[PDB]
Image 1 (cartoon, rainbow over the protein chains, first blue to last red):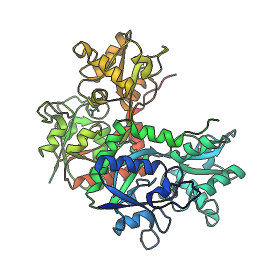
Image 2 (cartoon, protein in one colour):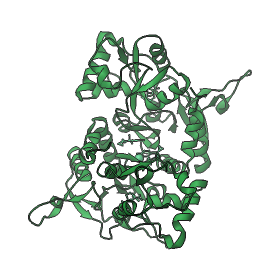
Image 3 (cartoon, chains in turn blue, brown):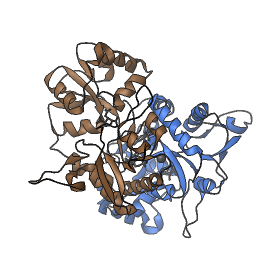
Length: 253
Length: 254
Ligand SMILES: O=S1(=O)NCN(C2CC2)c2ccc(F)cc21
Ligand SMILES: O=S1(=O)NCN(C2CC2)c2ccc(F)cc21
Ligand SMILES: C=C(C)[C@H]1CN[C@H](C(=O)O)[C@H]1CC(=O)O
Ligand SMILES: C=C(C)[C@H]1CN[C@H](C(=O)O)[C@H]1CC(=O)O
Ligand SMILES: [Cl-]
């Protein structure tokens, strides 16, 4: 029995391994999520085949309430597990079964260093500095749904002018921050990774919410609870902490 | 059916209300967990009866492998939910079904201010300053079972001399920190609560692990996934954060 694991390319979770000759199967990939999969399969004793999600999406609902991405792969039983930086959210948890979190994160702000900006409130009350998030990701959704006045104000701005302040993916966001007067609303784990490698960038303020990434399984999956117990074991042994350090640590600034 | 909720007195999660007359039922109690219970029952539409765990324990095993505390109340179906600072752990998650976490924490160190101690390593390296944890809690268990060299060394110390370095509860640990040359290994959420109120105490170093508290339900319970979904809703609405601020805010310290 070989489990199908849906995932998505995202540094440093899942990356194409560098090679001068064609690579095949699981050997095509490396990263934090490949290391996690190895540790999980060690503990639980399953074989697995990693498969990139065909539409290249994480999982959001459209106008008609239809799902896409890795979430949809789980719902349709085309995958057994999703192992990726898949944010645990209310809307997703209703349609798939998440394991307990293997990594914590919060939404925060990525911006260049040396400015007087110190919080989301600072961005909210002005219009000169543009700010946004990855379109249709869980960060954008948090702002779209929030009733906290500061975050409603930010969503009004982000969604204005045909969402010109939003970006298609994190890399586009990062380049926009580097080049123009732009701040990106980004998950703190990704911010840590980026600021380890771009000495001109920094996190602005603290975390505005509190959540995590979990392994996704279809509703009713017998693996969900086993995966959860494996994750708790890895946490208590210090292994999740070591894995993060391995993939996050940059060359120093 | 009205759900039976097992819990335990622990400030500021669950406390006796102050009044001029005897109190009865749920009206006996107030605190973070009662607020959480109220929000959960409002979302899910259940009634509830809060019942203090008869043995006054959180949940661990004896040599025979029999569980006690709130964990045991769930295993035997004497309670439908456990709402308390019940730490999500490997051994416990095997025998009950935890919801997703409603609060994060990690083990850290409570000590007096103004000293050069800055990490668990600084403590493990010496024998002058005593250090310990609450007996039989998840913090003690972390040390007992760790294979990390520094934490092994620390467990050797803690367990020595018939565990004279351990304490029976947090209040005892806090007084020992205040009175003697002693550092208490304590969940960061509780450290935060104490240090907001006593400027003589501080947290030393960072969190040495990463976990959370979850609502406990018996294995197979239909309520676990519903409670999880309610908790995500409360988190995303900013309500869990507000609730923490309501109960944790002291004056703070310079
Ligand atoms: O999305 S969760 O399962 N529940 C919400 N929480 C916050 C502690 C309330 C957290 C905090 C850290 C996580 F890793 C996961 C979660
Ligand atoms: O006990 S858990 O469900 N899984 C372990 N983790 C650590 C992020 C790995 C966390 C982190 C924060 C929590 F609130 C719960 C948990
Ligand atoms: C990298 C992307 C687009 C993902 C990763 N976690 C979030 C999710 O699971 O929706 C997205 C980021 C974000 O929305 O800030
Ligand atoms: C207050 C107590 C004894 C509890 C709270 N959570 C931990 C548990 O659920 O085991 C214990 C604290 C600790 O072990 O530091
Ligand atoms: Cl769960």
